[PDB]
Image: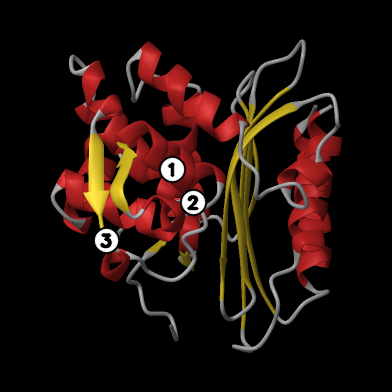
Amino acid sequence: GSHMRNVAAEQQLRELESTFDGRLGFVALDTATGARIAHRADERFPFCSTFKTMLSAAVLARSAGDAALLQRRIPYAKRDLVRYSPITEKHVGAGMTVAELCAATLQYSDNTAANLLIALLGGPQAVTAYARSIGDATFRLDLPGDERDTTTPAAMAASVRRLLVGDALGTAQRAQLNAWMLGNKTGDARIRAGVPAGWRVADKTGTGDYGTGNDIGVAYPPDRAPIVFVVYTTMRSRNAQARDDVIASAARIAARAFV
């Protein structure tokens, strides 16, 4: 890699953004060197389901010195279900364990699972507090540039790096967060589609209206240092679809520059 290849990649990201009516927010970090490829890195974007990574980390932190928390079952009822709950809807009544809820919200993006975990922590402000505790002053869990439920690509990249690769969590908790995110089921068309097939990817997607299409995580090449990938996209038209292809293309541009 080189600075000039990174400069080239950043122009390619700008040219990629021109292909849709919106904004591309991107950070890729080669942890071998701290080399960063960035686009609109300091702008706020709606995070959508990508916050579930920060959620799950906060839950893992509560479990330090209390591993049995992960086996604790949380009951809930039908009235507790919110839209898009493909796992939790099958377990109304007795409910699911804390670990099951983390896996459901990370791997299937289950919304009720996220709400139950947010409640366990004491509310959305507890998730924001956790973010502050690992050095993230930007993340906020609470539309024409409403800052609620937003972060920046730079801030989320730093948090993803610290959580999955660095020391924000204890070693065992880092391992568990990675294991869950390596098993993601919702990201096949996003970062995973753009990086080499030989790289293991731990990722969390986010999708919303205004063509909001996000994917964050870490790629683990087989004989190199990990590369952090954060991709946020959002558009001017509320009706617009998220663009899996753009997310994949952004990751590809960075992967090409770093090899």
Q: Closest to the observer: 221 or 24?
A: 221
> Identity of the amino acid at label 3?
Ala
Please give the label number shown on residue 53: 1
In the orientation shown, which residue stands out farthest toward the front? Answer: 93
Gap between marks 2 and 1 measured at Cα = 17 Å
Quadrant in the picture for residue 236 = bottom right
| Mark count | 3
Q: Is residue 24 visible?
A: yes
> Identity of the amino acid at label 2?
Ile
Q: Is residue 139 visible?
A: no
Q: Of callouts 3 and 2, which one flags the residue occurring earlier in the amino acid sequence? A: 3
| Image quarter of the N terminus | top right
Gap between marks 1 and 3 measured at Cα = 25 Å
Instruction: State the residue at coordinates (30%, 57%).
Output: 115
- Look at mark 2 in the image and give the residue it sits on: 87
Please give the label number shown on residue 77: 3
CB of mark 2 within 8 Å of CB of mark 1? Answer: no
Label 2 SS: loop
